[PDB]
Length: 339
Image (cartoon, rainbow, N blue to C red; front, side):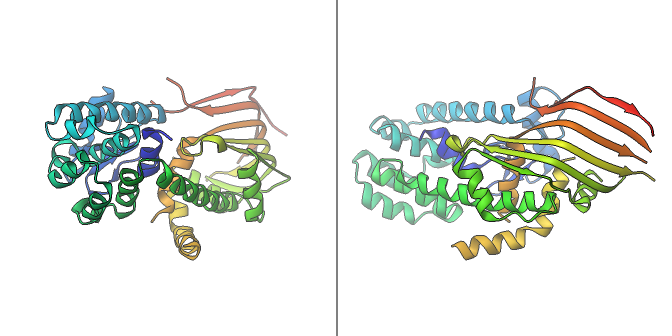
């Protein structure tokens, strides 16, 4: 457990512009774009960071760079701030990380107003500090996160964020079951996803696509889609820094005539209710989970067959993965004919 992992737990990951815990405009892994309530004025900081017109969208590596950069700006601010630095110097890696988390969240200037609790931390009076922090606007903003950071301050270890990691695993399992369930016509039991989490791999064979799903996502008409094999893999060893591997072999699409964000929208309609019900029963959240999920996934596809109408396109192999304005789609072995 490092600071990056706990911050990844607290912020998650998002590709589109989202309103943070404070209500301000934010991108990536908790990178606050602007305080202004206008999206057009929010577009500035991002483009300034990259140096090219983006319309408010970035890549995963850019979000990671912005993440590390934001942590660097955080420690810069801590060392610059007069009230925080003595409190920080006295602390160990874990509590230092909690302080860094707070400064990361609420900015350098705002955090320095917690004079009472800072003074309480220099004297290493963890408990009364915790009780006092429990009564604060920061607790009102992020009660869960505040509970975790406070717990970190109190115990000085990594116990609080492990449970949150567990929760993330469970949520991810539900979201994945719903997603795969949506894409396919097959009934995916929680036990198979449990297989995907116990062992790094899960393979399903002789499936059939949900043409409604494809029609809604791609937005052109799909009549039928059959996939011979679907292989899914999770970075289970490091579930927080998520890496998903999706692979389809023997794809067979049939299309009639007469981007990914929409997927997130579709589920949001159909699943957010059921998902929230499931989470509540387990004791708009699905959007974040799905966003990080689809942002983390790398795609492989082999021996595909697509029909259009009828023309026939045969694809030997194709990969969809990140490279150095977005993810690269490298395709090989396309042969198109008739019958």
